[PDB]
Length: 112
Image (cartoon, rainbow, N blue to C red; front, side, top):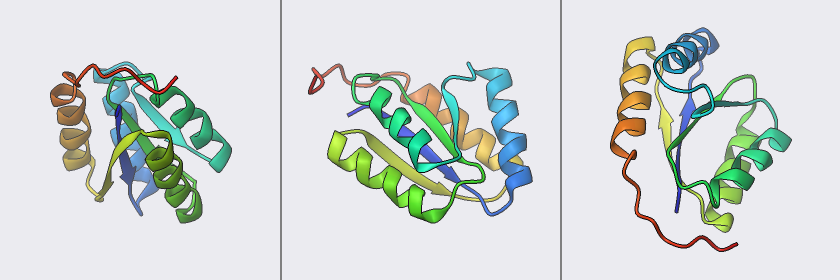
């Protein structure tokens, strides 16, 4: 419950482009980056009760903490979709449409 879009791209320059473009259009809180396992922990801490769509760009972080994101999310009841794509326009359209369509999430009481 409470879903995030995990944007993985081999092209860090493309991550930077889409990130700032989506932060231009939407609040730069809904767009977030992971730079460490510790950062990710703080993300998923929020997303348990925070029932709005998030977008985490794997910027500088590694596959070990990417899987730690998936694990901590699946145990803490945070929903996610793993988006593995490299394209500045396509990533912008997927990020933004996610924030638009998941703008209406179901209001279930969170395990607090």
